[PDB]
Amino acid sequence: EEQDARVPALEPFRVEQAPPVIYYVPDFISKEEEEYLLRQVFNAPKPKWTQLSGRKLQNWGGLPHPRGMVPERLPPWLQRYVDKVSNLSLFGGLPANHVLVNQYLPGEGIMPHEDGPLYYPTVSTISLGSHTVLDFYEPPRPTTSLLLEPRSLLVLRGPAYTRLLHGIAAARVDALDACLVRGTRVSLTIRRVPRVLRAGLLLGK
Ligand code: NI
Image (cartoon, rainbow, N blue to C red; front, side, top):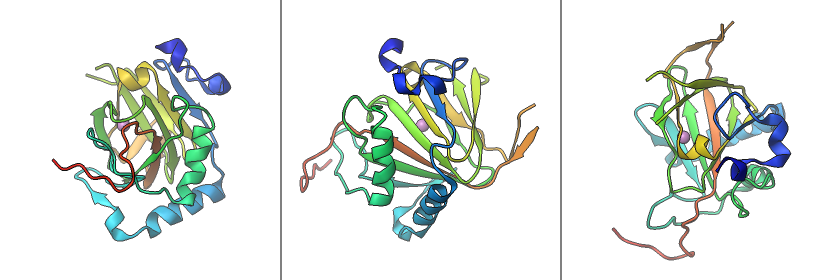
């Protein structure tokens, strides 16, 4: 599982003290690229947002579903980054086809979870706006935590996808020791959904 999950080109960005296999690439995007992404996410039609209890999100590329995803064309402003991460060969030899945008106001997070079998077992996430701390849990207290800085790419593969839980604490500040105040964070999670329906086909139920 671990040998299969290594990405030779990302070896210099391996987070060696974290569970196998996590990559963290600082400055994966420029400040101008980050600003344009934030502008496009915020200028999206109001109906693109789903309000949850603890955050709000957008699905781009379709709604993943165990009976098959009805696809939607990704816009070029997201396809550019889907291509960049798919060129790192992260999704088993086929390109990513889905982007989940999360917005976290200061104080918001996400309960510990695994991303599960609707996706090829790789998470790639580009962070925008503000830092956060990602907590990892054995399937309590976190086993490891990682600071995610704006404009970074995080990649979780192998057991870091299939065994470990990840979460973000509903916190306003992160003490590193020194102390970072959270702003609004927007994350772009780029994954490959293997079960996609042909164009025009609907399944009921
Ligand atoms: Ni997740």
